[PDB]
Image: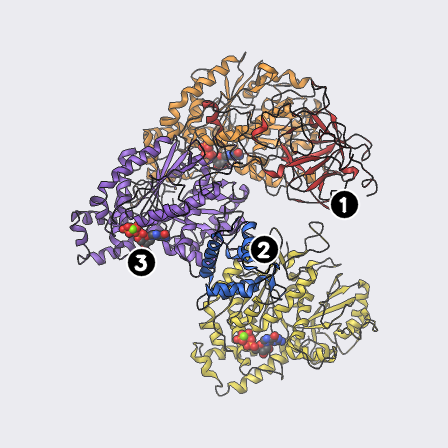
Chain colours: A red, B purple, C orange, D blue, E brown, F yellow
């Protein structure tokens, strides 16, 4: 508890322009909780990955802080993060000695979520494709003309996996660990089950695959938040 | 690209269409005024309402149905009701005078001058549609205008269209509780008219519906409104496969084969479960295994005939909710192992399992609570023999002295129609017995 | 270089397809967007086998999705991994099949065959040297068995030399999902014998038995069944994309798995499988791998290989293992399981070696074996027709397509003796 | 909103629901009173908005939170927030 | 070979279970007018 | 996964049934509201509520109980009582007319119009249960409804399920403090029904409880609430082992194989200790030394039968608290040393031992305070023959010349049946006399 509850100070946000380097939190807008990490508990994984937990308490703690370090050199040398610009979740240097990265693997009958039964999200030390992520605007219609646009702190944020294209969200499922009671974290697509006749859209050509025609519910809603004061 | 045009005729048809359309509109989220909230039009191009709705291009959503009736009372109520602005102000055709429980009247005298408009309207409605999958017709057999226009419309559509599949959700007379006294006639004649011109029919008798509500929902004084609501639930369950994605999908064409080994006599017996009220809802598990078992209990049956009397030919299961597919197959095993239901010797495999994800939707003012699973019952067995004979016996008893006949003879009907039709009724009281029985 | 093509049809055939490309996309290190991000330089050398080069450096699968109902194909593209397939390659009508084998072969399915035959020919012509077609579909479904087979039938009239595969999910009598389940499969089956070079039969019961028993899972979803079948797919061509000590293309297996020209129906199995709660408690190495793979229950066919004798069998070990251990276990299994590697063909087991283990596991194998034990499946499954044929009918839903009786009485005359061909090559001895 | 007669209409459907659920030989007021006496546990005779909503859902009359609040305020003239079901059931019996 | 097939001649005999819509297999023997039905592939 | 279905029928059982559940409710922390908040425990603990409660998926627990009685008077108070929100709304079967303390009415005419619902409820109840270990039924024998419906219900189960063991707690008339005037008639005919149908019977005569209440509790004006409290303890006393950790768990299946040497001799009497109030307890020591010694005190037995008047045939004991097992052996050994308590010649080992750690739970406001130890003594002895004899003596005098016979005769029960009862009841007695003879 001591180290985990060690002092943490979230960095300020200027002009609401969250930029790589500012120690930020990850909240669940619909689940009203903040993503929390654990180093003690060990997942059933031969590699070194560690479980994650979403916590209702919003008091700031180091274990709930991550780092947004540029994932790959790109044309966007200016520091403002752009939609669809690759980036990685980085853990605070205080939680663990070795740099820890959150990662997820594909569906598998052998590899499956402990509770949700979906693709699990892993806090491991792997250094491959499995680290990338890219923001995407909440409004379904704007999904197209947001490419390359600035992201503003305080605006709702969804998450999807570039290696697999699954959204990281939270659901009302209980979980057990030392740090009291908590919910689980996993990646999935809670797409509105209603179907859209996309086939005829192409041949008739009224529409293109790029603009999505399937509503995405709230349970995937995440909103980046900065510290209260500078 | 897939749509189904719903055709309604008669008092019962009009009311059932009203309830079912309320259910469909609420389930798809279209507000009563016909204008979707301006926050969920992302899929407006394709969406799912195309199955029952055809966008006007400016926002309004037109139901793909037509209402016909010769009595202005019900048609007037629809216009003055809270759904006034939804239906098209010409597709609810209005009659002039009532048929008054005379199947002869509604088929050769008062309906000739109006059937013409129905054909034109239906053709115009179908023209906009692109992938017509089938037609649904709800009608009240024991009602004059219902059977008459109901029969004439089906006969005309036969020649007009041909191979298009179409299902008949009739409302046959109750076994002992009665509303009309001449129901045996207008019931019998309609039978022949539908027999060789409709491909599939399902019984929806009343008393069976009434008891189901009393036993489960605990409403000792139910009105017709409670009756119509369940029927809408059955329609939604049957059609949900066409508008909600699922692992196992059943289309209207998936029925003419999987349950129809023969063309001429097309009949069914259905049931529903669960039907649970709030006061008795949260306190129970509502497991998939138990729900399916409750389905085959004769007490919950939706027609006044105990299925145990004979042999089951085929049965189609359509689930909606959070059913785990592995659970579905296990459940069927228990049904087959139970010795209380014995399949007609030939059934080799007459189960068609349908799995859909979207849960049933609850409408305000209804009796059903909120549930996470459901099962639909559509299976025909030799048990549909009681319904036909029982109607017939009354026919002979009341025809043995030429009673009530003159109401028919002087309206244009020849005398030979009755003689010929009853021969079809004999041709139906000597059908479901050859395999009802080491041959 | 010796690339192949895939034609998957029917909702059943489509759903399996939906994951295989999911499975394949991982092995070559490709995510949904169609961009390369792999790790190992060997990952990309043999990539041309399943993808075609495209502008912008992006790759697209060489796949043709074929269906007669609109919902299925509308379903896939809007879901995860929905961007890989070329939009043009899609083909669909406005009618549907409705598990009516008649409608899917004469009236509706017949009229649209032009497009699918139009698209299939073009893609095959593009490849430098077409290795062969692999056809996946469900004979229990309408479009797959009914219209899907014809494409299998027709394509033979244009490409006599290339070899075929079929991952057909034949339905089992225990739990039938359709009453028609037993007038669409066989009528597609009968046409299958004269054209299909090889046949893989995957029985649903095996999947549920496979999932519940070994995986120790509680509430599986079709996503569980699909992937396990898909994993088998990677085994067939696994050695076709990575270097190894002992390689064997899909041709080489064909030579050493079919004892006689027409007896081309196999049973397959995938190992090793263990539950989430059991991984640590098991020491995974070469010799206990054989125990799982040769176990009858591991088979995906409802038939029990203990009901008969094995004619020929092949196994593709996955994972980097030496050459000595692979052979020796074969000698013991042959001698110990001699009673079944029946007796007139010595050492009827083929061996393969590949050095790319499935990501996240250090040893696994794929099984493709021929054993008369398949005879039961073509004897019992729907065996009721022989008694249920006598009464002549259900016809009115199938003569609506011009089908006559002679097309049926003739089939057993052509079809009477599969086991009467398989049975004979089970008691014979020198 | 819900100021206009829509509140009265909701009462009409509600009265129908208890009328359908009413047992023979007893008025609707007793049927509504028994449900209120079933839901309440303090036995004081006053229930909160949550209890009123639970009673409505049991009868099958489920509406949005705004409508439930409006109905409660319509009969809660004092604005204290603890409506008395003794008068609430009596009004239904009169109607 | 062996395998299976369909039946496909309906409007033939038994004169009653003919075209009785109800998945009723093919038709009804009634040669003796007694029990077992025709026991789709 | 180990669950037992409880059956309650009749006025006598209902209140004793009422007492058992509350303590059962208390022991798990499920407040009458239907929740188990605990120390905010959600998934962070074992699953022990299976033995007597079932999970509904989200929230509350539904007890595995079915209630039967022909007079709605008793059911109503429970339905509107302090636990109104716990029991299933419809599983509380309610009758229409009182059994009027006549067996013939309760077994042949009015009792045959309600059993159908009972079996239907039970059959569905067993479906949810997966590890059914047996049945526990509470009933009264001195009442027409009690013996009648209870007997018929038990008979129905005998064929429906068969090998499933049954344990029933009845309440026979007191030797002299007795209320009913026709109670003996119903009892004997009840004995025939359960003689060859039930497995383990636990005598629970009422008068014995009074002395236990008065003498030890030092209460001179006990009420029906007090007596019910003791019974609930024993009922919770006997089965508590199956659901909590213990040194040597003992399953309900391990009574027919350890307490009934012969098939017909299956009637057994109970006793409880220690018994101490909330005033004079902390100054007393309560050691395994004397607590076991008091349990064998004849005056402390839970039934009005002197164990000093017959040999001991087989015994079974369960310990709870912090008892060190070796302390268990020491207490037993001296008991054998004492010559007052004597066993039969053919039982070499006659002590079955079991230890469960959990301390008995205290329901505030009662008579028994929080002690750290206790023991339940359940033993079958040949001395119970007297009680059956005493009832027989009552029957002969009141049946010599047809006392109140016509009331029973007119309902349909044959006159010769009583001759059947006398034959069976006396036959059992003569069976017991032979068993006690020495080899
Ligand atoms: N279950 C149910 N049955 C209805 C309903 N409305 C009408 N019916 C049936 O209709 C019968 C009464 O005659 P109708 O068929 O309604 O008469 P109609 O269709 O208006 O024909 P006409 O009276 O000649 O104009 C009753 O016996 C009912 O079975 C309804 O809302 N629910
Ligand atoms: N100790 C005890 N005995 C009871 C209780 N209730 C009923 N009895 C027994 O029941 C016998 C009389 O039967 P009733 O009072 O009529 O109850 P019943 O057995 O359900 O018979 P019915 O009134 O017809 O329902 C008495 O002699 C009691 O021994 C109780 O609460 N405690
Ligand atoms: N293993 C497996 N079987 C499937 C899947 N989808 C469908 N099936 C099987 O396919 C059968 C139905 O096929 P059908 O719908 O008639 O094929 P279609 O006519 O092309 O749509 C069912 O019995 C299922 O067992 C799947 O994703 N996995
Ligand atoms: Mg009318
Ligand atoms: Mg009583």
| Chain hosting mark 3 | B
Please, what secondary structure does the residue beneath circle 3 have?
loop
Label 2: few (<14), some (14–19) or many (≥20) C-alpha neighbours in 10 Å: some
| Chain hosting mark 1 | A
**Does the beta carbon of the residue at mark 3 sit less than 8 Å from ligand 1?**
yes
Please tell me whether mark 2 or mark 1 is closer to you in this view: 1
Q: CA distance from mark 2 to mark 1?
A: 33 Å
Which residue does the numbered mark 2 point to in the structure image? F129
Please, what secondary structure does the residue beneath circle 2 have?
loop
Q: Residue at x 61, y 43 (%)?
A: C218
B143 is higher (above) or lower (below) than E11: below
Snapshot quadrant of residue C286: top right
Snapshot quadrant of residue B352: top left
The image shows residue F418 at horizontal and vertical percentages of: 49, 79
The image shows residue C420 at horizontal and vertical percentages of: 44, 30
B296 is higher (above) or lower (below) than A150: below
Residue B85 in sight: yes
The front one of A88 and F382 is A88
The front one of C250 and C340 is C250
Label 3: few (<14), some (14–19) or many (≥20) C-alpha neighbours in 10 Å: few
Q: CA distance from mark 3 to mark 1?
A: 68 Å
Q: Are marks 3 and 1 in contact (CB under 8 Å)?
A: no
**Does the beta carbon of the residue at mark 1 sit less than 8 Å from ligand 3?**
no
Which residue does the numbered mark 3 point to in the structure image? B178
| Chain hosting mark 2 | F
Q: Is residue B56 left or right of residue C204?
A: left
Does mark 1 fall on the same chain as mark 3? no
Which residue does the numbered mark 1 point to in the structure image? A178
């Amino acid at each position: 508890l001591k180290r985990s509850l060690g002092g943490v100070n979230l960095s300020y946000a200027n002009e609401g322009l969250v930029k790589f380097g500012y120690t930020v939190m990850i909240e669940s807008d619909f689940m009203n909780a903040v993503v929390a990490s654990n180093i003690w508990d060990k997942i059933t994984g031969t590699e070194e990955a560690y479980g994650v937990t979403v916590t209702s308490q919003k008091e700031p703690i180091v274990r709930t802080a991550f780092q947004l370090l540029r994932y790959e050199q790109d044309q966007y040398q200016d520091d403002v993060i752009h939609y669809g610009q690759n980036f990685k979740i980085a853990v605070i240097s205080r939680l663990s000695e070795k740099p820890l990265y959150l990662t997820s693997s594909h569906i598998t009958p052998q590899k499956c979520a402990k509770f949700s039964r979906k693709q699990e999200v892993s806090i491991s030390t792997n250094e491959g494709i499995n680290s990338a992520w890219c923001f995407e605007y909440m409004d379904p219609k704007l999904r197209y003309e947001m490419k390359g646009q600035p992201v503003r702190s305080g605006e709702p944020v969804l998450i999807k996996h570039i290696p697999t294209c699954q959204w990281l969200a939270t659901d009302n499922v209980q979980y057990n660990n030392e740090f009291g009671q908590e919910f689980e974290v996993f990646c999935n697509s809670y797409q509105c089950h209603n179907k859209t006749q996309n086939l005829i859209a192409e041949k008739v050509g009224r529409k293109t695959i790029e603009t999505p025609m399937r509503n995405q519910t709230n349970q995937n809603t995440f909103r980046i938040v900065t510290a209260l004061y500078p | 690209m897939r749509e189904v045009i719903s055709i309604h005729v008669g008092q019962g048809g009009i009311q059932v269409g009203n309830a079912c359309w309320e259910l469909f509109c609420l389930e798809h989220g279209i507000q009563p005024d016909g204008q979707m909230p301006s926050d969920k039009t992302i899929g407006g191009g394709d969406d799912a309402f195309n199955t029952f709705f055809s966008e006007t291009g400016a926002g309004k959503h037109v139901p793909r149905a037509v209402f016909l009736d010769l009595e202005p009372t019900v048609i007037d109520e629809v216009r003055t009701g809270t759904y006034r602005q939804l239906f098209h102000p010409e597709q609810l055709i209005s009659g002039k005078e009532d048929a008054a429980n005379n199947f002869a009247r509604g088929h050769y005298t008062i309906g000739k001058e109006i059937v013409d408009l129905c054909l034109d309207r239906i053709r115009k409605l179908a023209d906009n549609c692109t992938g017509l999958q089938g037609f649904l017709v709800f009608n009240s057999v024991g009602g004059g205008t219902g059977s008459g226009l109901g029969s004439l419309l089906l006969e005309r559509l036969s020649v007009d269209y041909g191979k298009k599949s179409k299902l008949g959700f009739t409302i046959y007379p109750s076994p002992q509780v009665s509303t009309a006294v001449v129901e045996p006639y207008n019931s019998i004649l309609s039978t022949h008219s539908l027999l060789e011109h409709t491909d599939v029919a399902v019984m929806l008798d009343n008393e069976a519906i009434y008891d189901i509500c009393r036993r489960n929902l605990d409403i000792e004084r139910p009105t017709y409104t409670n009756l119509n609501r369940l029927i809408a639930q059955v329609i939604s369950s049957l059609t949900a496969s066409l508008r909600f994605d699922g692992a196992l999908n059943v289309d209207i064409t998936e029925f003419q084969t999987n349950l129809v080994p023969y063309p001429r006599i097309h009949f069914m017996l259905s049931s529903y479960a669960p039907i649970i009220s709030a006061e008795k809802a949260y306190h129970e598990q509502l497991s998939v295994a138990e729900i399916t078992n409750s389905a085959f209990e004769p007490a919950n049956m939706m027609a006044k005939c105990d299925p145990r009397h004979g042999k089951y030919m085929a049965c189609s299961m359509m689930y909606r909710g959070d059913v785990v597919p592995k659970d579905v197959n296990a459940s069927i095993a228990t049904i087959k192992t139970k010795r209380t239901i014995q399949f007609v010797d030939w059934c080799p495999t007459g189960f068609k399992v349908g799995i859909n994800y979207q849960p049933p939707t609850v409408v305000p003012g209804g009796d059903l609570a909120k549930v996470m699973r459901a099962v639909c019952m559509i299976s025909n067995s030799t048990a549909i023999a009681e319904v036909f004979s029982r109607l017939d016996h009354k026919f002979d008893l009341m025809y043995a002295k030429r009673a009530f006949v003159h109401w028919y003879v002087g309206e244009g009907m020849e005398e030979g129609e009755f003689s010929e039709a009853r021969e079809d009724l004999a041709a139906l009281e000597k059908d479901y017995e050859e395999v009802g029985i080491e041959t | 270089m010796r690339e192949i093509v895939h034609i998957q049809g029917g909702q059943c055939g489509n759903q399996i397809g939906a994951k295989f490309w999911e499975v394949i996309s991982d092995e070559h290190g490709i995510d949904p967007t169609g961009t390369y991000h792999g790790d190992s330089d060997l990952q990309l050398e043999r990539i041309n086998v399943y993808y075609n080069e495209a502008t912008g450096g992006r790759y697209v699968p060489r796949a043709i999705l074929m269906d007669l109902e609109p919902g299925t194909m509308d379903s896939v593209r809007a879901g995860p991994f929905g961007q890989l397939f070329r939009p043009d390659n899609f083909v669909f009508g406005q009618t549907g099949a409705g598990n009516n084998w008649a409608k899917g072969h004469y009236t509706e399915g017949a009229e649209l065959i032009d497009s699918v035959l139009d698209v299939v020919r073009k893609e095959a012509e593009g490849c430098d040297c077409l290795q062969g077609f692999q056809i996946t579909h469900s004979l229990g479904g309408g479009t797959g068995s009914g219209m899907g087979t014809l494409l299998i039938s027709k394509v033979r009239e244009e490409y006599p030399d290339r070899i075929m595969e079929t991952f057909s999910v034949v339905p089992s009598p225990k739990v039938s999902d359709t009453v028609v389940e037993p007038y669409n499969a066989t009528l597609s089956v009968h046409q299958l014998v004269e054209n299909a070079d090889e046949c893989m039969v995957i029985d649903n019961e095996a999947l549920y038995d496979i999932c519940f028993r070994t995986l120790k899972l509680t509430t599986p979803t079709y996503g569980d069944l699909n992937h396990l079948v898909s994993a088998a797919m990677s085994g067939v061509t696994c050695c076709l994309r990575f270097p190894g000590q002992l390689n064997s293309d899909l041709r080489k297996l064909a030579v050493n798995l079919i004892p006689f020209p027409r007896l081309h129906f196999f049973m397959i199995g995938f190992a090793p499988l263990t539950s989430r709660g059991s991984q640590q408690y098991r020491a995974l190495t070469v010799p206990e791998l054989t125990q799982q793979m040769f176990d009858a229950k591991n088979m995906m066919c409802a038939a029990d290989p203990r009901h008969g004798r094995y004619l020929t069998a092949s196994a593709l070990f996955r994972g980097r293992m030496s050459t000595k251990e692979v052979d020796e276990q074969m000698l013991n299994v042959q001698n110990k399981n001699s009673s079944y590697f029946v007796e007139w063909i010595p050492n009827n087991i083929k061996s393969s070696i590949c050095d790319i283990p499935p990501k996240g596991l250090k040893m696994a194998v794929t099984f493709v074996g021929n054993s008369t034990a398949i005879q039961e499946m073509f004897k019992r499954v729907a065996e009721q027709f022989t008694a249920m044929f006598r009464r002549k009918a259900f016809l009115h839903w199938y003569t609506g397509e011009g089908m006559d009786e002679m097309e049926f009485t003739e089939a057993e005359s052509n079809m009477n003796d599969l086991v009467s061909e398989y049975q004979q090559y089970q008691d014979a001895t020198a | 909103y819900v100021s206009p007669e829509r509140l009265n209409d909701l009462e009409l459907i509600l009265y129908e629901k208890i009328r359908q659920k009413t047992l023979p030989g007893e008025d609707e007021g007793r049927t509504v009173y028994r449900a209120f006496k079933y839901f309440d546990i303090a036995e004081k005779g006053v229930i909160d908005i949550s209890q009123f909503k639970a009673a409505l859902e049991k009868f099958g009359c489920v509406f949005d939170d705004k409508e439930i609040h409006a109905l409660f305020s319509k009969f809660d003239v004092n604005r204290s927030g603890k409506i008395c079901y003794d008068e609430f059931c009596g009004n239904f019996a009169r109607l | 070979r062996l395998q299976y097939l369909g039946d496909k001649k309906s409007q033939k005999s038994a004169a009653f279970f003919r075209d009785t819509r109800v998945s009723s297999c093919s038709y009804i023997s009634l040669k003796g007018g007694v029990p077992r039905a025709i026991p789709y592939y």
